[PDB]
Image (cartoon, rainbow over all chains, first blue to last red; front, side):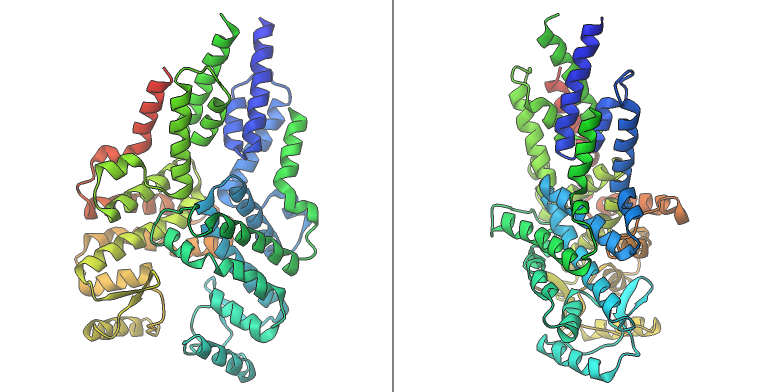
Length: 247
Length: 247
């Protein structure tokens, strides 16, 4: 009568622990959703559901959104948190694809904070401000020339451009060294994201390269946003601790 | 009944629910710890293979066995992943991936029908402007009308593939279908490159995203008419197999 329900409930509790350990919040919700008298069930369901929704729609976690004011900080940190969570569960193709856009976002954001007016945003895309001084543009032209490219003020800025801009404005920036781990997976990422190839982790030191690109993002965050509190880099661990206390 | 029998039946129903939501990794998690679970070894093996194939973008064996053409297989496989994540309401991820699949389909078509038009450098597509001066002239006129300048150093993406087809084959059924994918380009930029939150209820984003996914399916029917209709529903078929092991 009650022995059966006690067994079922204790077993579900351990199952949810395993799933939560693998960041499978939607599966955990699935196991608890129909359980009537389960202790902390309502709060558990609410928290698992809001978390799954935040991940699916790329909504910054409420704790983060409430603690910090800078929108670029919050987005960078949030997408790092998702990135590291995907790596930790070995969603490796997804990790490989996302890392470059995060790196690009951090560098763009960094430049826009420290040299505002250098870059302008038009229709959601970054470009050199056409009001920029020839002193800057001349050096940039020289860097493009090393890269076998011509100067075009109307061209959309991408990762190579951000690296060149930073090379001119702050050549000692540690960002310029951290980004190399992101460049090292560029061809692999092209292969997976655009040519739809299989990711062979056991070839070309890919396990290691992908890991190092994720660590590179974390290091870039420490450099660009030193005001991020260290505990917020461990959001998922903290969240799993909270879930364990409810169970 | 034997407690083991009660545990086995409970796990059986839990796994069926997880499978029904395409949570194969969670299903694996629940069955992995069960030693004497009927067909447990075969299930564990099958769920692991599927999980790994999804994580590394390895074409499913059944697809690899039924179909011969590499581009067909990659296109269909990535549509299957796209639609499976979309069915799970991973809408931001869906929005990001749909464009790359459409680009792959058009690029494949262009490389068959105008093989000298695109030159591939380090796995990336670029307009071969030296061999195709008549095309380059028309393409430049097209960009010039849009107050955009022609830039041979740019990697070709969906807008360029669409322009290529508009010039070379304006009657294309592919060109009609891909418009729904072009329509989510700015939204995708916002989510993928600016790290914004996806608000499905704004500007009927939900509709736009649905139409982009259907566009891929229509394009596959155009390019690869030999794909059997049931293969667009791989996961349903796969779940049937799992259900037979769980009976």
